[PDB]
Length: 132
Image (cartoon, rainbow, N blue to C red; front, side, top):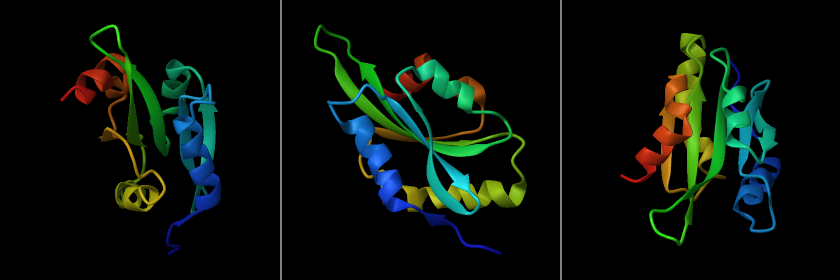
């Protein structure tokens, strides 16, 4: 059984991309390429991110959400571990615990989520949770 590996250089670059004020990329994913975690799709629109979250896949994501009650909006970042509902038992556990490895790269975020219900990826839901 192969232990998980991570391409830290490639992953750190994707993470930095979301953090950069010079970037129009608000979401990036990290997926398994064999047993190595590498960057997956990336985008400017959150809805396109939800489309990546199929019940058959497991991925991690780093997202920049725009929040704010007053006139002065504030960016909030989230780490999301998405584990599709059809993911095998052994791999679901491996994924759940691989997030500490991913957090060695994704070091800063307002809140982290572990989600298996597609309804919780809705921006309204995520943002209401970010306010707690």
